[PDB]
Image (cartoon, rainbow over the protein chains, first blue to last red):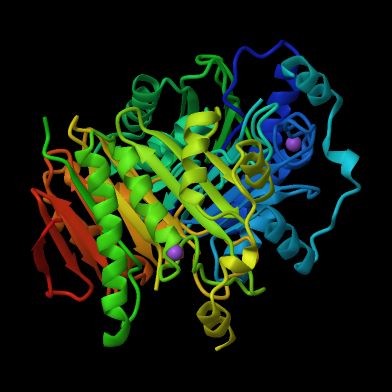
Length: 296
Length: 294
Ligand code: NA
Ligand code: NA
């Protein structure tokens, strides 16, 4: 059976301050830790990617769940998707509000509906009827994002996991872009763009310019290069190089193939990433700054 | 310059009676004529597919705009997306309500926002700012759709323009008795459609859950990239949706060179194509009729 790997990413971003850097690290370490803990228990790659992304929605330092950036009405409006590489099973939610973990609802969508995608009000109603709690507004908005919205008037989190059966999965979550139009949907809930998972190829989770990821369908394009016999690095190189020259978009991504190979590449300035494989934790934000430590 | 082309499709769905096929035929013809008239009058590929889809939305017979199917709540909710293959610019709406033409709303997202994809309450609010009328929701509700709910498919258009640009537009009401705010493939780029001047353009129809799963539109084009012809590539992607996800449906594709095809694993798929002063139509596998264009 395969050696389990979890890969986690923060938002593709510009320069990070020496400070966010500290809490970002531990945020990335915490999520990669849960994702892996899940696979050591023999959990599925779906359970692990879900697990990792929940940690990031709950961690205020990351643009998803609590800590999401604000829309043009100052409100939190969130998107998420998860994909099961076994039979291509998927669930996704767009434009959701007043809920803690949009990724759990995407999972509920995949696992307890005949659908793959619920939006806005019907997304709230499905959460209401599945007994997801409504949160007393306020809670989701952080003082850092409050200033951020006044200023203009951070990025998508994801996870890719490979389990002992060779199953792969991805999960993505985001509150979008600051001052975005109400009801704007980025790449996250769109399968092929914000992510793709296929036991025959691998799984990808992306970040960066949402519309640009959509226009190029980045996650599925990365995988297309792999199917053609490229390495995980060359595929990510090539698919991001394309998003750069064709539509002028920047981002980043995390991929893992069906054979245990993984990398994290980006064209934005920063992308906090973490990976757990064989009880070693890898972490980085800028290229080269990579640390490797034990993971008991 | 290229000889321009438009292809249209109705839904990749089940059997259609003799009595109503003549009527779907009237619809397809009107839509293709509308697309090809824009193309022959110096209009863009994007112009041409919006014009063709707008027409099927306006026709209460097809599951887009007027005549959408009703969700679980006896309500109409519409998905749409349109794409320009030159710069890969795109527009898309999901779960839009009380407006006549979702594809027209889709193009305004493309042109008028720094976004590509709006949904539900935000799109409705955008529609208003764009002066798009808020029209009786029950005027989108036909008697038949109130009935069929109690007891057809996604439409679309591809085109290649004289300048050599490709575009797709796709609009749906979705599937009968869907959950509130269920989004299919139709506003998801690469599933609902894809257009890229450097390959061609595809529009898809059928069970939307399956189409999202396999990235059907971009896959078809992946095969076209590999040297597979349009029919070949269409057969592989549609074949793979059926094998891998047990999903049925159809698609239309126009390549950069101007080769095109209509293909479906579903029973029926209304379709009409226009090029070289001729109209091509069909609903059933192997029943094509080639007439002269007016
Ligand atoms: Na968060
Ligand atoms: Na219609």
